[PDB]
Amino acid sequence: LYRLFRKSNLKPFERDISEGFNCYFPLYGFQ
Amino acid sequence: AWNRKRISNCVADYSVLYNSASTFKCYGVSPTKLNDLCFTNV
Amino acid sequence: ESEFRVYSSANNCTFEYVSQPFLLREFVFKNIDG
C-alpha cells in the first residue's frame, strides 16, 4: 500500500482507496 | 555546471514544466498544484 | 563620455530590477518585512 498522489482533496474521516503522465493509476517496501 | 541558476522575483510558471516534453519528477511539491507554490528561494 | 563606473563588484549577485524612478525630489525609503 502507498501514499501516491491524489488530484482530489480528502474530507474528514473519508476513506477513498479507488494527470502526471502515466503515474496516476498505479498504487510500500518490506526491507 | 550545476546549481547556478537563481530563481526569484519571477513568475515561477510550471506550464513550461508539466506541459513540456511528452521531464518532471516533482518530489517535494505537489505535481498538479505547482502553480500554487511559492518559496523563499529557487 | 558619460559612465557610472561605480564600485559594483556584483559577484554572486542575483537581484536585478529595471524601471524609471527618476525626476525638488522628495523621497521616503523603508525596509519592512523584506
Image (tube, helix red, strand yellow):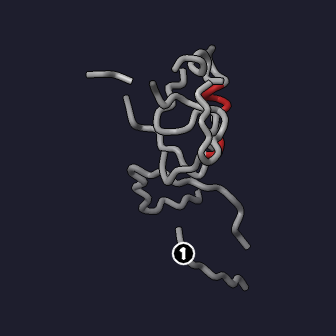
With respect to residue C19, does A9 lie above or below? above
Residue B14 place in picture, x, y as percent: 63, 34
Residue at 55% of width from left, 75% of height from top? C32
What is the x, y in percent for residue B3? 39, 36
Residue drawn at the location 67% of the way across and 31% of the way down: B15
Question: For residue B17, what is the image quadrant?
Answer: top right
Q: Residue B15 versus residue B36: which sits nearer the camera?
A: B36
- Could you tell me which chain the residue with mark 1 belongs to? C
Of residues C31 and C29, the one drawn nearer to the viewer in this rendering: C31
Comparing C13 with B37, the one in front is: B37
At which x and y percent is residue B26?
A: 51, 31
Q: Is residue C3 above or below residue B17?
A: below
Q: Quadrant of residue B20?
A: top right
- Tag 1: amino acid: Asn
Toward the right, the furthest residue is C23
Observer-nearest of A25 and B21: A25
Classify mark 1: helix, strand or loop: loop
**Dot 1: within a 10 Å radius of its alpha carbon, few (fewer than 14), some, or many (20 or more) residues?**
few
Q: Quadrant of the N terminus of chain B?
A: top left
Q: Residue at x 65, y 45 (%)?
A: A11
Above or below, A24 against B26 in this view is above
The residue carrying mark 1 is C31
